[PDB]
Image (tube, rainbow over the protein chains, first blue to last red):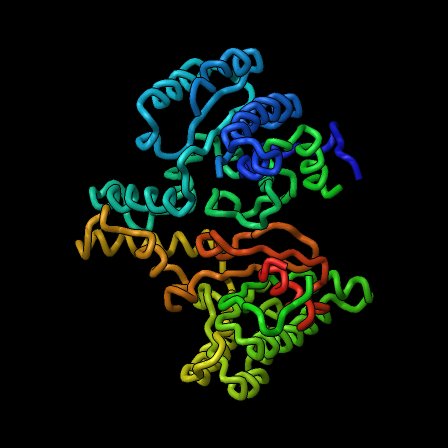
Length: 217
Length: 223
């Protein structure tokens, strides 16, 4: 049962990118060659997901100059760039390149490309917890006024509008069957899809196959 | 691949029991027959999991709506004693019927001193609500200056989840099983399932057998 271009498209897709190392090793390449091939794979699926109607494409690394040579194609595709995680541990120069790509695409109105870099779901839930625990301690609101919407606001997806915060479809590559500490709160009702294909071999056809199964075929 | 009876057994196995209604529809029985049959499966899987050495078995249910647990627990308590199973139920028992609340509170009390497998029921349970309840507590306690905000740790959160009663090694499931062909978490142990192995079977829950549990464990054994 095939993918329907006129069928239902998940508005928010999250992908756990995996297999970059195993890709190079089976081809006996050094593992940097598998990571280079994975970051061009990122470009190929950012472009295809955008053309399919996806509104948020969240990518988990389970950069470099990469953002500088990507920013023109992101602007041609009307793609807005966000970065989830702890920018603090990022090198200062890649901190600079990331906030530059964010600022240079802040006005694009199409699909949001949301990078998960040095990100952890339990860590994210903890940092959301400390902020709420501090806010109630400065009497900003009760402890009983806290809601799920409160928790969702303090997650790294809270910048998104409420209808796009949670992925409707979560894809996991490299043949693993684990959530692996990714978007634990947000994937409460997400459809799950697992492909044995490694991320450097992940193609738009693989994405369409995944969306095909999301459409319940 | 094949199940190795001498191989590794997951300490904590979580199952999302799904497919009870569809099971009845296919037989054209009333859909209540699927849910009453699914409870027979609960007794079967509890016994087989206990015999395989599973330490914790968390089951997710998915007025007669909620009248099911009164006669289930009451007639299930003897065999739970014989199998040395300690019963626990996660979720807000506060909200469900009085009559079902006492049958559940009795089954917990009558099995409190059992030392074998923990049968962990999720009735009126939701992971997101469970995390909200864990934070409403932690926010309150740190507002009582029991500690400070940056001393909150993941174990602070883990203690305040509804699996916190379990020791640390048994809190998180190592294998999550979803029946009825569906491939989604559906708001179940969201924090705890962070590293769990996921197994999906098309089998409807009333057809879930000890062998279906064993193929799931076989997959956890990395085939």
